[PDB]
């Protein structure tokens, strides 16, 4: 389906990312862009872990839930989420982050399949805003942590 790319850069340590990598079950504070979350049931191998990820959507205009195979890696420092059951059509999600100068660059790929073509663009449209809040959220938290 339509994949939205969200790239951001923050002059912070890769430590803060550690929490973002596990944001699927981390959240040192909270996340309005999201609602319900749950990660478990799977397997753990080496510096890699794969389990089901049941996330929900609050102010998404569509109160629904979705499950996907969340794959975390501490050796790869990357996150990947495949579709398992979701809406029973398709739903991909992945999070990546790498160093770039004095600051680090993080990219978030959002992939989902909707029913309504109108809501498809409508949602995929506000998707940017949602990513804007999530981003600002991380940035705020970053400043709240570093607090200068």
Image (cartoon, rainbow, N blue to C red):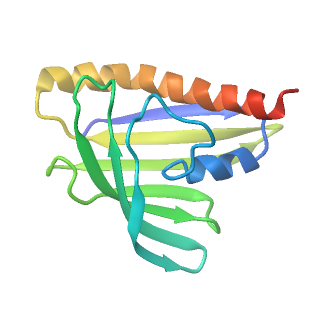
Q: Position of residue 38 (x, y in %)?
A: 40, 54
Name above or below for residue 48 compared with residue 88.
Answer: below
Indicate left or right for 68 with 20 as reference.
left
Residue at the right extreme? Answer: 148
Residue 141 lies left or right of residue 107; in this view the side is: right
Closer-to-camera residue (25/93): 25
Left or right: 86, with 16 as reference point: left
Q: Residue at x 58, y 52 (%)?
A: 21
Task: Tell me where residue 34 appears, x and y as whole percent.
Answer: 41, 34
Q: How many marks?
A: 0
Hey, which quadrant is residue 148 in on the image? top right
**Residue located 22% across and 50% down the image:** 86
Q: Quadrant of the N terminus?
A: top left
Furthest toward the left, the residue is: 116
Residue ranking furthest to the bottom? 45
Considering depth in this image, is 107 or 15 the residue closer to the camera? 15
Residue at the image point whose x is 73% and y is 33% from the top:
142
Residue in the foreground of this view, choosing between 87 and 6: 87
Point 76% across, 27% down: residue: 143
Q: Quadrant of residue 42?
A: bottom left
Q: Nearer the viewer, residue 71 or 121?
A: 71
Residue 125: image x %, image y %? Answer: 32, 20
Residue 144 image offset from top left, x and y in percent: 75, 28
């Amino acid at each position: 389906m339509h994949r939205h790319v969200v790239t951001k850069v923050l002059p912070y340590t890769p430590d803060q990312l550690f929490e973002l990598v596990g944001d699927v079950d981390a959240y040192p504070k909270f996340v309005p862009w999201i609602t319900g979350m749950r990660t478990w049931n799977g397997r753990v191998d080496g510096a890699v872990s794969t389990v089901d990820a049941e996330a929900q959507v609050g102010f998404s205009f569509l109160r629904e839930k979705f499950a996907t195979r969340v794959r975390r890696d501490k050796d790869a420092r990357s996150i990947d989420v495949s579709l398992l059951y979701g809406p029973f059509k398709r739903l991909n999600n992945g999070w990546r982050f790498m160093p770039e100068g004095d600051a680090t660059r993080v990219e978030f790929v959002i992939e989902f399949a909707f029913k309504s073509a109108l809501l498809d663009a409508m949602l995929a449209a506000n998707v940017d805003r949602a990513a804007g809040k999530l981003i600002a959220c991380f940035e705020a938290r970053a400043q709240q942590l570093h607090g200068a």
